[PDB]
Image (cartoon, rainbow, N blue to C red; front, side, top):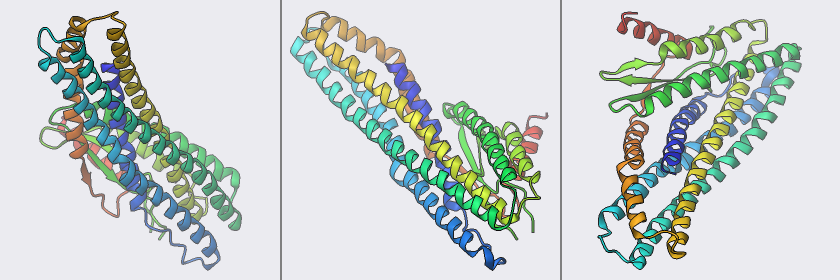
Length: 361
């Protein structure tokens, strides 16, 4: 259970930094301006209404959920510091009753923290559910606009699936970068937000879902930009290839892709939250089994003492080490401003060229 707890914590913490950055990109998205086309006023208002709801979903995550996930790390640290302390306090000839008191104190903490993880899982499950509905309904606003300007709905839908497909690649590259950097002592996570497509001027730039996450090592040395550059540039390319689509349909499409991308992050958060809740479940079960087996007299104090002792010398070390690195990295995220005349792909491409020069390669 100690390693299950470790893996749950690592997966939820890394994914939490990913959806956090995605939510920031949704919050920073500027309303769409189709002022130059009075006949698209209705579409402009439907798109800004859906965007407002997306910003509220993102805000809900940042303010109401992110802190519970960070609280979970702290709860893991307190749990294991407490289990460890039991090991150092219980003297030699401690009675069954004293051991039952001690087991009780750790089971109470574990159940308290299991319930916090469970409530976190429900809250993210609900947000994911709402995002599935809102992102699915948003697509009708885009088709409707495409119909108002007699665009080809086949070409639009193809672009939508192509962007979904490249977003899996971008997500997987960001996930691998963050997982790989989460447990580096002295390492930091670096994020940037920027337009998802190449810029062209009077169209509203879409930063929603335009994210980069990279690592920084000793001396602020960026890692991950070379890897990430490939999938970011590919998205920019896929948009470039549909410059025959109406400009406003393209913007509307970019928000839709950002709305679906947000729902994808929330599904990843559900999966991580489930894995963490299952880890707590197996921790409380183990304690309940030790509580019953000591009472049934199937085990004894001596076994329990050695069980907690070994744990404290072994897998608990890894968890406690992880809790400290994870809190530093989640608290030390470095936010890079992207200039208004650079896409997220442009920005990372420039960081990738700097990364090549630092590697002399």
